Length: 307
Ligand SMILES: N[C@@H]1[C@@H](O)[C@@H](O[C@@H]2[C@@H](O)[C@H](O[C@H]3O[C@H](CO)[C@@H](O)[C@H](O)[C@H]3N)[C@@H](N)C[C@H]2N)OC[C@H]1O
Ligand SMILES: Nc1ncnc2c1ncn2[C@@H]1O[C@H](CSCC[C@H](N)C(=O)O)[C@@H](O)[C@H]1O
Ligand SMILES: [Mg+2]
Image (cartoon, protein in one colour):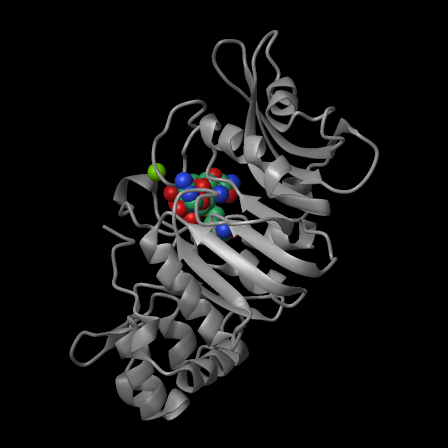
């Protein structure tokens, strides 16, 4: 089972982690097969070669944090490395649902896509709801005085702190908790790579939590959002005959009474039962004329392996 490994950033000093991060930045996500790159790709590596690359300091940092395991004559990693838009991010390997631990962290299914979708504005205070590996938070930290990442998965919170230290980022905070419970006051930016996919209304697990998690999210948005604030959400939406997602959403948001401008970009569509239709898209609340707008944009087909 994958996603249960111990993650302990507190067991390594910040300077060492930062320097590991700097070594990752050079080799992770490129074509050079260094020990480090191999390690964070799922390939076992020779510790003496790893030591050549990142030093005994680096080698010990990999082990003490849980990034690598000493299997005797080789090291392996439970984690996989990524380098996105200047940021290095470790997460779990992408594996089928049936072998995921309950504390499995989103292996960056959509994150590289989402960052390209995200508005390139900055501001005071950002919130990354369901931060998982921390990836969206790490990106937002460049632009915001302060970023708060929230997850109900304690392993995600630890992984987030690890990844922030690897990148030397210190204006980010990560908190374990349930949706908005640990998020006090208001935010100028809220990002939500929602745990919704094929489960419809049913709660399945942390990565497919059901439509009610969106209702909870959107019902609270008006009181968590600063004036002129921006909300961005990746989500699956179910339309049923006589019951479109957009109208339930409008009700949750109190869309008209709150003067929110909503724009939905629908990328993928699927047939579902009850004559329903499933869609995946990118939802943006941004300052502008009250109302909801939906447009077609097959950005999965277009980008996926691109910008
Ligand atoms: N935030 C995410 C959202 O981005 C989305 O992610 C999807 C991802 O889970 C799916 O992953 C499935 O297929 C993979 C093989 O391809 C299998 O290893 C996987 O365990 C399985 N799950 C992807 N194929 C498509 C993604 N959009 O739904 C889950 C939410 O928690
Ligand atoms: N009730 C809840 N409160 C806070 N986070 C939750 C939650 N239920 C599920 N989540 C989290 O929502 C995340 C969805 S996957 C998104 C992970 C990350 N932000 C990324 O883009 O890669 C998971 O990390 C899951 O643990
Ligand atoms: Mg699952």
